[PDB]
Length: 332
Image 1 (cartoon, one colour):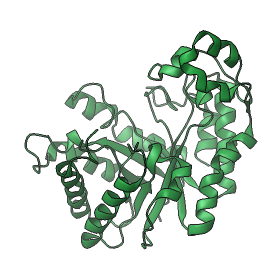
Image 2 (spheres, rainbow, N blue to C red):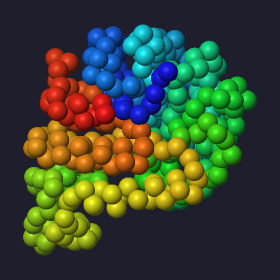
Image 3 (cartoon, helix red, strand yellow):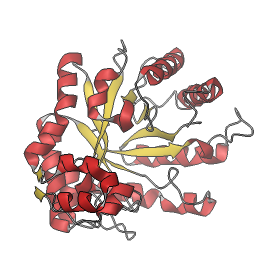
Image 4 (cartoon, rainbow, N blue to C red):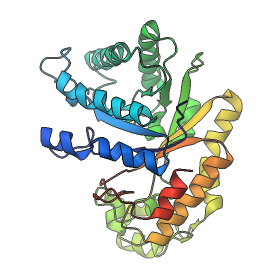
């Protein structure tokens, strides 16, 4: 039996790669990595991929077997170590996806193709449709998601599909998803609360970079009022002034997902959650311990971000954990 409860992400491999290089692709993740993950106790891996490894915008419809090989081999390694694999589309075609039906067509076609390609794999693979959803409302995503589900179901009636909502799969956007009468659906949400703690000093976040402050957990945001005074552009941060960071805050942020499930009686999954590696170790470990305990209390499976690199590393390049206590907590 394969399970999808205590996983880890393989971001930075065939998704969010620096340069499109075969050297990177052949070496970033190898069988030794899957072996390490399996020996640690995780039951599955989440594999983000960006469309270009599979389809070029030029010869649309012509799928690259060379890119597909990275996915095929990962499936092999997973089957070998009895791990599940959640195949996740990070960057879809198009942002114009919800504007251009051609982009919509390619998106659906790519999933139709993958459903066919992996039709004989019944227990080690699951599909997670799309990660990047940031829209004014869910109307357009709901339309595309339904077509995609439909297209896939004509080919595979029992393939498990992972579906997330708007606002980067926010837990409070699940309620805005169209009702899918389907029993093989798992609802996904990401969780990085409190943001200025999990992304403190994240170089890719303008506000976090402007704030440029170390934060501990449990603890409290400090100097917000002083920061806003100097930077009126970030006035909205005044809402966070002196916010107390503790386990009850995390429980409150998780509430919307729990309420949705209480109504839908569905399965929930947290595909991404984590803390930036530069945070102090003690706080980093404590946040995971508290969050994992909430996931276990509510029986919600998930995958921590990230296996290696991507600034959220759980393992060094030497395939050794940054902290053994941390890995133990995450493997449940």
